Image 1 (cartoon, each protein chain N blue to C red):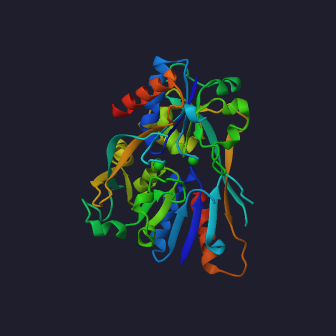
Image 2 (spheres, rainbow over the protein chains, first blue to last red):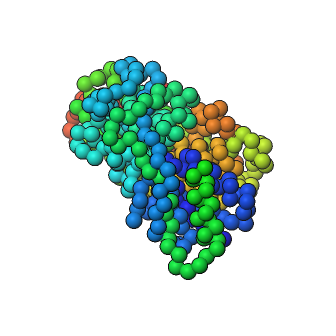
Image 3 (cartoon, rainbow over the protein chains, first blue to last red):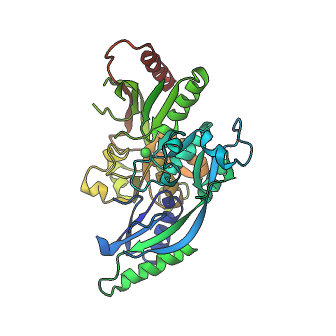
Length: 192
Length: 192
Ligand SMILES: [Cl-]
Ligand SMILES: [Cl-]
């Protein structure tokens, strides 16, 4: 059987491998296919920081942080809320449907702070590493790459300092043991 | 003055910072804005592995390689051409206009090898690092992240083993010293 999973970026950088590897081990017969952005229903599961409006299960909340180069010329510790958009920002392309960065660049003034739009947070962190730009990232992602990319990881002094991870699937249009098995697996893997 | 540069992924992971930093230093008055995918003309420059068909200057050729986890269970050295699509692949979303990965997944059989599509090669390498999937990447990118992502970097035994980097801009519809200055700067930075 084939399952088509959408694990929306940037969550594909932690959860896709966990899911792929676990199903590879316990059900080598089952073929899981992964995409990392949205856009056959009964084979579909979405894991995302959005609810796309299918079911919707909130799994966990992730802290979001501010990242900058370790050797930033002026940033040497936490910022005030008013300071944030006086920095130059790197973000994920705002034109992308459900872009990760959208919540924090929803006014002209905030958008004006952006000097670079990349295709994924992983690209964003590479540019932050190499420049004086700042970015807003999940703590887990920033902390994974802080050592190799020489990043400082700071609290985000904005009201929107978390995102909620949701698991979503097509409501049972009939009984389906394999589908229910995958529902249970994905909750377990995500909650772990 | 504002220049709008598109440095198409994955090249934004090496060239965007070089350009941003150099112009920041030598012309702090000039505002360079960056995007990393295509889709005001006289302020526009594109740097990409495509010619989008504006001028078109071929700058350099980059070797493309095969990447896999260092501790891959079966891959322990170079592959034969026929072996490549018998592995499970991670690639950049093929539906994206001018997706980096498109040249290598242009048949049903090749597409069938894909288990994961991500939004950028930087995301792809993170998943390769964590799984048994393989991917096709620029050598410079793979070699930058091989140590931290514990990757092996292998020659690509396919005919399409290089991509050409092009610089492209709007033909002079009138004389423009600032535009010509930026043309000269970008050739210099890219060729260096
Ligand atoms: Cl992302
Ligand atoms: Cl890419």
